[PDB]
Image: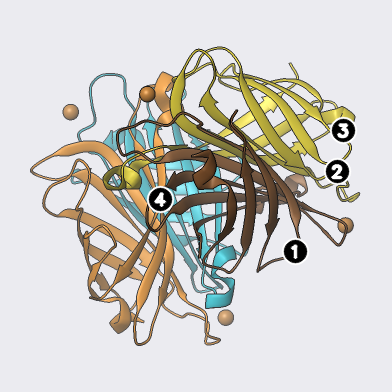
Chain colours: A cyan, B orange, C yellow, D brown
Amino acid sequence: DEAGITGTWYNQLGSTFIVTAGADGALTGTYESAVGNAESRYVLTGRYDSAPATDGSGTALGWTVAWKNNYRNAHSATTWSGQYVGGAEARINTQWLLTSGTTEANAWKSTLVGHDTFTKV
Amino acid sequence: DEAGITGTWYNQLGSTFIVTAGADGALTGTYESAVGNAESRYVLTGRYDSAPATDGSGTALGWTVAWKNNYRNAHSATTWSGQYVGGAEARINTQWLLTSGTTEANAWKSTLVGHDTFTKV
Amino acid sequence: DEAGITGTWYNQLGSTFIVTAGADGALTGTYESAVGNAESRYVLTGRYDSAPATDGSGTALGWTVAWKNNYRNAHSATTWSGQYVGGAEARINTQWLLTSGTTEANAWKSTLVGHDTFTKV
Amino acid sequence: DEAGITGTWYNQLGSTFIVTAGADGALTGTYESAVGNAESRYVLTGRYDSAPATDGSGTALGWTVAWKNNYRNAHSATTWSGQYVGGAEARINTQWLLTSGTTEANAWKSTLVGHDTFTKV
Ligand SMILES: [Cu+2]
Ligand SMILES: [Cu+2]
Ligand SMILES: [Cu+2]
Ligand SMILES: [Cu+2]
């Protein structure tokens, strides 16, 4: 799925995920969020299963974005964890964890959880 | 916290996380899990906030492991999302999402969620 | 939203959630899952915000199902946490945690996480 | 575990959970949080597996709190999902989802996720 994954993907929020999949399992690219304390592109990296099961199963993958770039710093990181499902309407179906840096006293409220679905259109 | 983060960390399961923090926000290294469908080391990559708040707050970070290496392939990926808290007993406090590749019919049961706390000892 | 919430709801898996909302914040009813180790109806209970904000915001709510009834026992419980959004196409948008009873050694893999969207049709 | 569960439990934040376990799987009680937009006690309800496995496994359970009482309304609900582990130092080990009522535009940031461990002392 190196070919399948590589490219430009869009989620339900209107965010844009630009990724390259390496033959060795790497994911590199940029993320631009349509929401939150974010502007322009941010580095991302991740990993995917470069030899998935041949049985109909999706391809596991994940990636991280730390919310610092030359424009802003939102003192946070999101990780998406999910699977790529190939075919006529290819999708990446993810769940994510967004942890902000907090004091000890606020750690209980440090982590948001949600779900993003990415499509090629 | 490039110095703070860089090195060998151990969680409550007895897993070993070996990371280098780059000046530019990169995280690279290897993960070896004490549990699950896993043996030996697996590549990991991630990101962290290289200019955290100076107010007492932790440092946001995350990383991914796809569960494929030369020994096995568990057709899955974990993402940890959390924060580094520096000082006498430094910690990385994380929550994680483990997504397995599944068919459409099994997607509902694709994703495990838990929490790992990493220490230097 | 006592009137709004009360009734029969269906999710994207084809599961059926039958609830009564009490004036005092109670949720009582039955759940029947279309997937998993489940058959027929199972008791559920929960709570919702009986005096929500008047600003356009959704109405917070949650409920639990333990997966035991007269037919089976799957030694697990799901909690859904989410919000009711009223209007022409009313929805309940949830995220859920399914914890199985496990030994200590398997606790790391005890908890599934997903997301369900319920509609009146 | 009706006897095991029933009573007063305390988490790592200093919150107090007072529960009765019914023979039929019910959980009823009150929760008082040490943190957040909360004061005094709030109703809770939930469910647990009243006939757990005899193999060493924990007992699955969950409960909800909507954050409305006579003192305040934080327009939110938490669900804890977890397991009771009996014996010399009994514990309830949970993960939780806290959903706030939000507008559509803020739904992405509606849900916090964390983990609480409850003890009898
Ligand atoms: Cu295989
Ligand atoms: Cu700052
Ligand atoms: Cu209000
Ligand atoms: Cu059994």
Q: Is residue D81 visible?
A: no
Give coordinates of residue B49: x percent, y percent.
44, 73
Q: Residue at point 53% right, 43% down?
A: D3
**Amino acid carrying mark 4 in the image:** Gly
**Nearer the observer, A15 or C40:** C40
- Residue C53, position as x, y percentages in the image: 87, 51
- Count neighbours of disc 3 (C-alpha within 10 A) and say few if under 14, some if 14 to 19, many if 20 or more: some
Chain identity of mark 2:
C
Q: Position of residue A7 (x, y in %)?
A: 39, 41
Q: Could you tell me how far apart the alpha carbons at marks 4 and 1 are, in whole angstroms?
A: 26 Å
Q: Which mark is residue A87?
A: none
The numbered mark 1 sits on a residue in which chain? D
Q: Are marks 2 and 3 in contact (CB under 8 Å)?
A: yes
SS at mark 2 in the image: loop
Q: Chain of mark 4?
A: B
At mark 1, the secondary structure is loop
Apparent side of residue D50 relative to residue D35 in the rendered image (left or right): left
Disc marking residue D38: 1
